[PDB]
Image: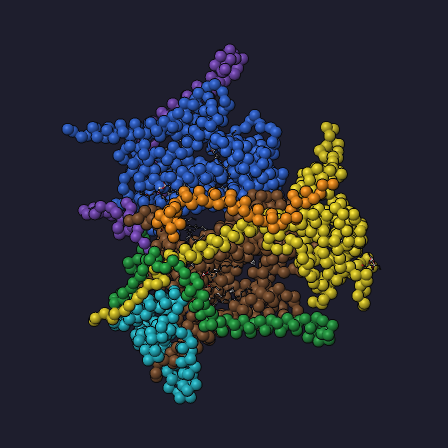
Chain colours: A cyan, B orange, C yellow, D green, E purple, F brown, G blue
Amino acid sequence: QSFTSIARIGDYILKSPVLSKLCVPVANQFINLAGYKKLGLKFDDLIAEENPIMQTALRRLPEDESYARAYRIIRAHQTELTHHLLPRNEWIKAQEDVPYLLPYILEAEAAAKEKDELDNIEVSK
Amino acid sequence: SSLYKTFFKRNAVFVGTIFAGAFVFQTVFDTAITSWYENHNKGKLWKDVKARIAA
Amino acid sequence: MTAAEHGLHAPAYAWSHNGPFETFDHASIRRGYQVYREVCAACHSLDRVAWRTLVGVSHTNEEVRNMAEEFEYDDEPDEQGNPKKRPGKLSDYIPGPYPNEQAARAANQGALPPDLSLIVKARHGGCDYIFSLLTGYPDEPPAGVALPPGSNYNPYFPGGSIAMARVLFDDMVEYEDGTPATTSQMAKDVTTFLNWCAEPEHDERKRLGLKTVIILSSLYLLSIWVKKFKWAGIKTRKFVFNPPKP
Amino acid sequence: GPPSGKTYMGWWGHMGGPKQKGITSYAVSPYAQKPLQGIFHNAVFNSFRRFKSQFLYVLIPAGIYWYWWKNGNEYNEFLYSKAGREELERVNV
Amino acid sequence: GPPSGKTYMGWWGHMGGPKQKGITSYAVSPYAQKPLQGIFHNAVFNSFRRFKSQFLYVLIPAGIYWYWWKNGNEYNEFLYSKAGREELERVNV
Amino acid sequence: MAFRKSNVYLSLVNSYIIDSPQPSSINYWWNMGSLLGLCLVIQIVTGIFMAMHYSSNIELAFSSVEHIMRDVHNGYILRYLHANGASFFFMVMFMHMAKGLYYGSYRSPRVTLWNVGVIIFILTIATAFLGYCCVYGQMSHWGATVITNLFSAIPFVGNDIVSWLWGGFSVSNPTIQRFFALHYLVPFIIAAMVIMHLMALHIHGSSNPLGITGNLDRIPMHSYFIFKDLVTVFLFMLILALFVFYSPNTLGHPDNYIPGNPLVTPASIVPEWYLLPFYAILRSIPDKLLGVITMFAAILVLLVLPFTDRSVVRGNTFKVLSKFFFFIFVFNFVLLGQIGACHVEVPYVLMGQIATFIYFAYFLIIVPVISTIENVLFYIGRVNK
Amino acid sequence: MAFRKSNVYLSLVNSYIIDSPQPSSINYWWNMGSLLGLCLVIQIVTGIFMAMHYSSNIELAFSSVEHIMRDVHNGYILRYLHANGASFFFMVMFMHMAKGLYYGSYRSPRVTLWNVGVIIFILTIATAFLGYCCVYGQMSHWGATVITNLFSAIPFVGNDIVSWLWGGFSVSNPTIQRFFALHYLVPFIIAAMVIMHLMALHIHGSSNPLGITGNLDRIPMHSYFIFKDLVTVFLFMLILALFVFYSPNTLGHPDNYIPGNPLVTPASIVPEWYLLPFYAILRSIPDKLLGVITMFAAILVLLVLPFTDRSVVRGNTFKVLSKFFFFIFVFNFVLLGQIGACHVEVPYVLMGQIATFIYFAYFLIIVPVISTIENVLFYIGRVNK
Ligand SMILES: CCCCCCCCCCC(=O)OC[C@H](COP(=O)(O)OC[C@H](O)COP(=O)(O)OC[C@@H](COC(=O)CC)OC(=O)CCC)OC(=O)CCC
Ligand SMILES: CCCCCCCCCCC(=O)OC[C@H](COP(=O)(O)OC[C@H](O)COP(=O)(O)OC[C@@H](COC(=O)CC)OC(=O)CCC)OC(=O)CCC
Ligand SMILES: CCCCCCCCCCCCCCCCCC(=O)OC[C@H](COP(=O)(O)OCCN)OC(=O)CCCCCCCCCCCCC
Ligand SMILES: CCCCCCCCCCCCCCCCCC(=O)OC[C@H](COP(=O)(O)OCCN)OC(=O)CCCCCCCCCCCCC
Ligand code: HEM
Ligand code: HEM
Ligand code: HEM
Ligand code: HEM
Ligand code: HEM
Ligand SMILES: CCCCCCCCCCCCCCC(=O)O[C@H](COC(=O)CCCCCCCCCCCC)COP(=O)(O)O
Ligand SMILES: CCCCCCCCCCCCCCCCCC(=O)O[C@H](COC(=O)CCCCCC)COP(=O)(O)OCCN
Ligand SMILES: CCCCCCCCCCCCCCCCCC(=O)O[C@H](COC(=O)CCCCCC)COP(=O)(O)OCCN
Ligand SMILES: C/C=C(C)/C=C/C=C/[C@H](OC)[C@@H](C)[C@@H](OC)[C@@H](C)CCc1oc2c(O)c(OC)cc(OC)c2c(=O)c1C
Ligand SMILES: C/C=C(C)/C=C/C=C/[C@H](OC)[C@@H](C)[C@@H](OC)[C@@H](C)CCc1oc2c(O)c(OC)cc(OC)c2c(=O)c1C
Ligand SMILES: OC[C@H]1O[C@@](CO)(O[C@H]2O[C@H](CO)[C@@H](O)[C@H](O)[C@H]2O)[C@@H](O)[C@@H]1O
């Protein structure tokens, strides 16, 4: 599933007071149960990267955040291999669980979509 | 452990010794097991029954 | 499936060979052979069992040699090409009662008494089933059950209707070692003998099992300790991040 | 040697990951660590950690299926007993 | 993959040969050539020349071995005939 | 460079078993592959040595297995190792496949790895089938009979294929002799397929329990994993030994201790345990043709997973709904097996039909629906607008 | 990149069969390899299909081959293809080896290539031997007896190994049955070695008739050599078809059409034609142990060639003395084969002993002396100082 699609559905719900009051709480619960923050990872660190869109995005990510991502990943594999969790003071907090890569992903997705449309445009003489 | 050092002194056991030990272990281990096994089954073995049947 | 069709579940008796460390009771094997020879042999074969296998298990070389020599077998034809017989030997297999299936069914009202060399392994329940069947014939079937002319009721048999009639009765045999030959005692003894026929490697199998499991259990614990050592440096590896200067 | 395709994994020296800077790691020789006693110190103590965190994801479906089995197993038992031949004639054919 | 052990052969583009310069090659498409029905009359006599430069390397040894065999086979025949039993008894045992 | 890297043969051993970069965090579930390699070797070695005392003729088949049990020195060890070994082979392959399901191992870029695996599963089941037939017991005869007849469901040429497979009017001498010939062949094809499996595994390396790149922290296969695998090798051997010497027949059927009889199908007939779930699936369809199709589709549907999983992350580790349904699936699979072991009776029939639907719905409905829902949940649970 | 180069599986096919850079000047002698591959496939396929109707029991073996000959549709074609196929396999292999000696294919950097080849040669011979035993004709029995007894020459454990190979007091049931099991096994081992053979060939590529570097002018395997190999494939099939359909038993022995008899070794006993040269070598030594050692050394001495060839150039193309002595070797090998078919009688015994000496002298004395001499001839024949 494309992030454009995920965002479209997600924004729609997030803008709707009725749906938003109903879903978001369930989603917050889901993310806490997911437990990746206890491993010190942000959600965007979990996205499978073995595809062109993600490679483009990870290429464009600024140097400093890229080094930061690398650390969270390495630290996580180590924690996971020891079968422990990180001390609470190292858990990613909700405020920190920011969609840092998402904008780069959406940008890459839009460019590929346009390129696909332009590659298959029909002409009306 | 000094018990280990007196025999191998900070070196790991070499193949030759390992193999040699394996040969000693087979003989000794087999005897010990057969011995324990036969004793646990005293009265049931054929050799025990053969002794009984004497007439 | 109805209870009758299923057949009554066989209870668990305390066979002295039940258990990782137990061999068969050889005195019981020896007694079982007698029951087979004097009570079962007349209808049931033991085709996969060779005389020589009884030696060192339940009889001496001499006892088996003498037992085998009581039977005739087809020998190699004479110089003229005419067929000739010979007394059995240790290399021969315990002779069956019938020349073919047809003769067998004729002597049993159409029914065929199966070969018992694997009966203990060829039936769910094993020894418990064989024993329960042999000692489970009531004097009469339960009320309401109509029995096919020529059949016998036994709750442990699927369907309840079996072609074999009860054959074990108190003191129909006289054990050589002076053991009281009661029906259940004889049932216990042949079943033990039949288990040996089916699994002659039993005793030796369990002995090697003890050896194999002690070595592997040790090997297993050893491998864990060794693994933990080779991984100690990685398991305790520490990381520190100092955001690089742009 | 012929040119094969690109993948997301390389080899020692060019594994395929992002550039790493600022991370420092430390380790100690296994030969310098306490002769393994962590089998009954931080393994039996920290034991049931993986249990109480995940067991619900396994236990609920396990329980759901076990109940469904036992329920259907008992219904079968009744259907084939004397008391159940009436309902057996119905539900069957 | 891992570092490859270098040999004396490479692949298209880096075959492992010396740098080539000053040599020009020309070729014509097989589609524009005489339908290969010109094997005879044009170069049929060209044959034999190939197996006239080599026949002695094969023939002399073949001749050497053929006569050695023929010579021994005839001796065997004689040794086992009435006439040869005289010499047979001597050379045998 | 080191001889292990420069030598034409050793460099292969080095790249796959020595310097191979493994994700530092792969857990014990990743030990199942090495275990399947052991199984294949165990199966082949024991089979060859038994092959030396076996006779495929339908009249000597059963007795020759009895000859191996009684007359061959350590023959009963060879047979129990082979027979129980086959069972362990399937229990380990089921765990290996389940590991794949749970951690999204089937996802790109490992689709080919997964597909070749599905190929291996099919060959392994066919091999096991052929081997069981060689014993020529009651279950062997009727199993050969039922399974070859599976092809009679093919319209038009159906019955000819079956006569061709049998080589006669029914499962008989030519059937057992070719089946033994084929039983000997396939293990070598599986090995060939295993090599292809490893070739696909190698270009991408293994995945890990986190489902993210393992590129930032790899540790060599040699020592770490060579010794970690040894741990499971010994536990596998210990447990197989427990069954081989102490309970060698609890995983089999007593009916296979009775020589095959062409005129009598035992009322107590039951397929080998590892085939029970597929058996239950087929038994749930009240139509001959549709029944075999659905059963075969039960294996082939494993091929659709790379496309039905809509998740933006690989693996179930951080997904509550996916984790719950993964276990529903696993337990539904065990129930399908238990149903297979029961008779075609009222409560059981409907349960099987329901469990069969749950089996297919997991790949075709639950996975794509739940994954899509989780994608959105991860999004709205943090992003503000 | 083209899919044939990018895909994990097709890239192997492409590097070995499609884009492989072949020396532009290799001649038809370089077509034997592919022909040997064809031979292996012919043997395996025809063998598997016959195995489906075979019975390894010593009481049933011979008759089961007769059953294939008479009762199996196209069964005589399977057997005649398999049997004659074996001989062709050996004739093509001898030419493949000869091609090697001639063009110096055994020398650096191709020694590993050559050594694997020697390994394959031994394995093939053992396979063919095991196969011949399965027919259980008169030649089968006695061949099995003599060949297994070859090991009784080993001091102390000698007779024990024989008893173990036999599985009893003499070549009997246990022997024929295990020999069939091993006959089925070795061909897959050979296939695996052939892969190792091709792996070693690949890193260095083929040599050429000029004995010099082929790096300055290579042409693709595909089209050129794919279609050139097809030429020899059809020729090979044409000649083989001629024997299979018109002279099926010319390369065989009539005695093998007689069931094995443990009490009578026919006076007409002769080994299969492809083993005669080696058989003649053994007979040439009036001592049991030395006889078997010399015969085995006759195969192993092939490993010495890389070191005894002192020449500074690879191949015999431009070497008068080496070309001559090479043919002395070829015809001496053929003669050794002829002596093999003769009785142990006066003229022949000496001829065999001298020919045996020439066989060994070639590798150990002639090659090194002649190559050294030619090294000096090439030098003084032009260098003016
Ligand atoms: C009938 C046929 C059966 C044949 C199959 C036999 C082989 C079974 C394989 C078992 C398996 O794959 O289970 C894997 C799970 C995952 O585990 P994990 O997250 O990676 O481990 C964290 C470790 O404690 C790290 O700890 P460790 O330092 O490496 O030692 C671990 C432990 C390993 O024990 C084993 O043998 C593994 C099963 O050693 C011990 O302390 C045991 C002392 C008695 O292990 C479990 O949780 C087991 C429950 C399913
Ligand atoms: C024996 C039983 C089992 C074996 C069965 C299979 C037999 C195959 C083995 C034979 C072999 O390898 O011979 C190789 C020699 C070397 O040859 P060369 O120097 O490389 O060739 C130059 C070509 O003519 C170029 O010419 P071309 O354009 O390629 O056509 C060649 C020729 C090829 O014929 C063949 O089938 C190849 C042997 O076709 C013809 O015009 C003639 C048709 C009869 O070919 C010879 O001419 C032999 C000389 C002694
Ligand atoms: C054709 C298709 C065939 C496929 C069918 C499936 C095969 C049949 C199933 C056989 C056993 C397979 C069990 C499931 C496979 C292993 C699952 C797994 O990988 O679990 C990982 C999980 C916890 O690991 P985590 O990494 O997610 O922990 C988070 C750390 N931060 O670990 C856990 O949650 C604990 C594991 C609990 C296992 C209990 C299994 C119950 C199986 C019944 C046994 C059958 C005998 C009758
Ligand atoms: C264990 C020991 C293994 C070794 C055993 C060897 C057994 C012998 C193998 C049987 C067949 C012999 C094959 C001959 C070997 C290869 C011959 C060869 O390569 O000859 C090349 C030669 C001319 O080739 P050039 O490349 O040197 O030409 C350069 C042009 N400027 O062209 C020629 O010389 C002409 C071709 C010669 C034909 C070969 C005739 C010998 C036939 C044997 C008959 C078989 C009897 C049953
Ligand atoms: C104590 C000696 C005997 C033993 C241990 C014995 C044991 C058995 C066993 C275990 C079975 C198998 C039943 C099954 O299918 O589960 C059986 C069947 C049978 N036995 Fe015996 N038996 C004995 C004596 C006899 C005698 C003396 C006769 C012949 C008059 C006989 C006739 C039969 C027949 C005809 C069956 C067929 C049962 C059927 O299929 O309905 N048995 N017996
Ligand atoms: C003879 C049977 C098989 C052998 C020897 C085998 C062996 C292996 C090995 C050695 C590995 C790497 C370590 C591991 O993850 O265990 C592996 C990985 C894998 N195999 Fe298999 N396999 C077999 C059958 C299968 C089957 C039937 C499937 C799928 C239907 C499968 C799917 C996979 C996948 C997806 C991986 C990658 C797992 C990951 O890295 O996440 N394999 N296999
Ligand atoms: C992937 C490998 C293999 C598998 C999964 C496999 C599986 C089986 C199975 C399930 C049986 C019946 C077991 C029983 O209940 O007795 C069997 C029997 C047999 N297999 Fe295999 N087998 C394999 C490889 C081999 C090989 C390579 C050979 C041939 C060299 C072989 C020869 C036999 C023989 C002789 C029997 C009959 C004896 C017996 O019942 O165990 N097997 N096999
Ligand atoms: C089933 C057995 C064998 C197969 C399938 C096989 C196949 C091949 C193939 C495909 C080639 C390349 C093309 C050619 O030169 O014909 C080759 C090359 C070679 N093989 Fe074999 N071979 C086999 C046995 C042997 C044996 C027995 C030896 C030597 C004792 C050997 C020695 C060589 C050598 C030295 C080369 C390189 C020749 C050169 O390039 O000058 N092979 N083989
Ligand atoms: C790949 C190398 C192989 C070679 C060199 C080879 C060679 C031979 C030889 C010399 C014979 C005796 C032929 C005769 O005089 O009747 C034979 C027989 C036989 N081979 Fe093979 N064989 C090979 C592979 C196989 C394979 C893979 C099988 C599979 C089981 C097989 C099955 C048989 C059978 C059943 C016979 C007996 C029937 C007959 O006489 O043809 N062979 N083989
Ligand atoms: C098809 C796959 C089947 C099996 C897969 C399992 C993979 C593990 C193979 C074990 C090889 C261990 C060699 C270690 C080595 O060379 O390191 C050597 C050390 O070796 C040792 O210390 C020997 C310990 C005993 C090894 C136990 C044998 C294993 C039992 C075999 C069962 C497998 C079927 C390098 O040592 P160093 O690094 O300290 O200098
Ligand atoms: C099913 C098989 C799939 C095929 C994959 C093949 C992988 C092989 C795995 C096993 C590797 C173990 C054996 C490798 C031997 C290493 C030594 C070596 O290569 O020394 C070789 C010489 O070897 C020989 O002469 C005989 C090799 C016979 C191998 C028998 C199995 C030295 O070769 P070297 O690399 O030094 O060459 C230098 C350039 N002049
Ligand atoms: C003993 C074995 C010796 C060595 C074995 C290797 C020899 C290879 C010979 C096989 C030639 C056949 C290759 C056909 C496969 C080409 C297509 C392919 O790989 O598509 C694969 C998918 O293949 C499958 O799903 C099934 C594998 C086929 C199993 C065949 C038995 C696509 O893989 P792809 O290369 O395109 O990956 C990049 C795209 N994202
Ligand atoms: C020459 C080679 C041939 C013909 C290969 C054929 C391969 C077929 C399939 O493998 C791919 C097949 C083995 C596989 O189906 C996908 C299994 C899950 C089949 C499951 C299976 O088992 C049974 C069984 O074992 C029995 O035992 C006594 C009895 C059985 O009914 C009474 C069955 C049965 O009703 C089914 C569906
Ligand atoms: C389980 C596998 C086993 C035991 C394999 C053993 C393999 C041994 C060797 O292969 C490597 C061996 C076949 C190979 O020696 C190098 C051959 C050249 C042997 C040549 C050979 O053949 C004969 C033959 O064929 C006969 O037929 C009727 C009769 C024979 O005498 C009368 C012989 C004979 O006197 C010799 C020396
Ligand atoms: O073969 C025995 C014979 O007995 C009959 C007599 O009517 O059945 C009764 O007696 C049997 C032997 O005591 C019981 O086994 C049976 O249950 C009882 O009804 C016949 O039916 C039977 O053929």
Q: Nearer the viewer, residue F246 or A64?
A: F246
- The quarter of the rendering in which ligand 15 is drawn is bottom right
What residue is drawn where x is 40% and y is 67%?
A83
Closer-to-camera residue (G59/A28)? A28
- In the image, residue G226 lies at what x, y percent? 38, 47
Q: Residue at x 50, y 64 (%)?
A: F300
- Pick whichever, A88 or F204, lies toward us: A88
Q: In this view, does A43 lie above or below F142?
A: below
The x, y position of residue G169, in whole percent, is 59, 34
Relative horizontal placement of residue F339, taking residue D25 as reference (left or right): right
Could you tell whether D47 is left or right of C148 in the image? left
Residue A93: image x %, image y %? Answer: 34, 78
Q: Residue reaching furthest bottom?
A: A17
Residue at x 58% of width, y 28% of height: G265
Left-right relation of C228 to G204: right
Residue F313 position within the rendered picture, expressed as x and y whole percent measured from the top left: 39, 71
Q: Quadrant of the N terminus of chain A?
A: bottom left
Identify the residue shown where x is 82% and y is 57%. C150
- Residue at the extreme left: G385
In the image shown, does F263 or F66 lie closer to the viewer?
F66
